[PDB]
Length: 111
Ligand SMILES: [Cl-]
Ligand SMILES: [Cl-]
Image 1: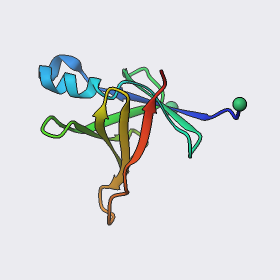
Image 2: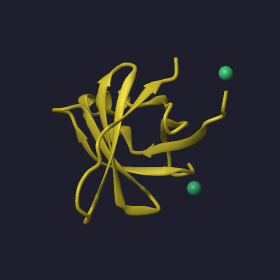
Image 3: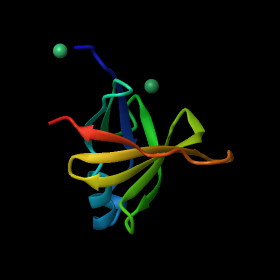
């Protein structure tokens, strides 16, 4: 079959400043995920100041199991990840000063 494109998302954050539940919630999204229709995979990991593909977390929603983040290189585009279960998360796109938020797209964990 076809090869996919793989995008790295290295979330940059100091764990020692978070609550246990905020850590839990980020951890729901760490992993390797794919969407068949886009032929796209994302690899979400905790990175650091040295990393490439750096993203900054804007909000950790422990009420609804979501995180919001933006790339270091563009503060305007906001990504939202919604937890479903251990094998499924959903991505939406919003923005700092635009109108609207996109419909969720399911990413499945690569067994
Ligand atoms: Cl095949
Ligand atoms: Cl980079």
